[PDB]
Length: 418
Image (cartoon, rainbow, N blue to C red):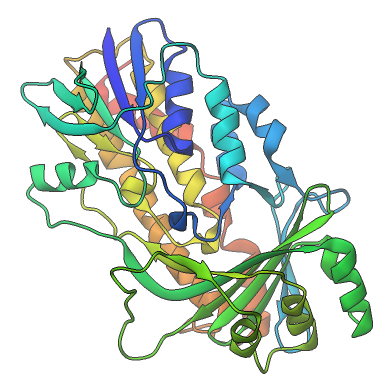
């Protein structure tokens, strides 16, 4: 048998726990970490690879209960690309059978938690000490209880407390969240209100019902409908690429209230469609976008990082949540295998570190490069609209259409399995 503990009740941690409990030879316990809010950033979305992992983990019922997808006949459109100056059409990116899929983060976490069998969740207590020696991990909690397991999963988010345990154990330098220099205004607009605002400037009503991204120099604005198209979610990005490589105040949360004036002034000089959209946003907030560096390793002994704890990224490819789900599916398939025991666990974790980390780190890198492309800063594309529109239609396929089962087949071959 295998005793597995998971620290962190986010999407990645609860998803892994739900699948790991389906195996009779595995005993799982799920513990809470520090709650988050400012770390949500631009939000949560699901690409084609994410929904595939969700189905592979058996979480389709919870996903259908809460996820938001664009109404027919635009169900497969990921985004339409437009110039921020005049809202002219540049192209579109299509995700067949998925399109633009998003969720309120708390809605999906709550839906997943309700499906947990009794006795798996051990909430209401926090880990105060974590030690390991000879293939076993010991965790001491605030209530005096101690949990000892063969494997401890660090799924506690971008400010993971367990990441320091992993980086120190491997002798690597510590890693804290890095401010990207990009801030994002967030808000929601009633769809009928936005239609009347667009019509007043002669803007097509098509731009309300289909997800849109308005591209400009050092900034971009995205919209997509939620709640059966009755509400339009808006994220307006502003990037400071000046000399300093900027920082965020150490005593400042990553989110604050924003004034309408400062938001409209930040997009002064943008087109009529973009400014009319921003004027519709009530009570806007501003979010300081952070990510994590590419870690040299995710494993130290019997402690392993997944999700944002291992590979927190910028949201420009909508790939953050999906990479944590790919971590959960990859690990649960190997751990759930009959041939998995405590004797080959170190071998199993080495396959995870050799096959999951290089892909996740590449997604971290490409997410930053994609943001540079959105804001007309790519060193080759620049503002070439023909090349920009063509590359935007294709540059996401390696992420969306990756077959994770080929990585698992390579892991088993390295383990001499099946």
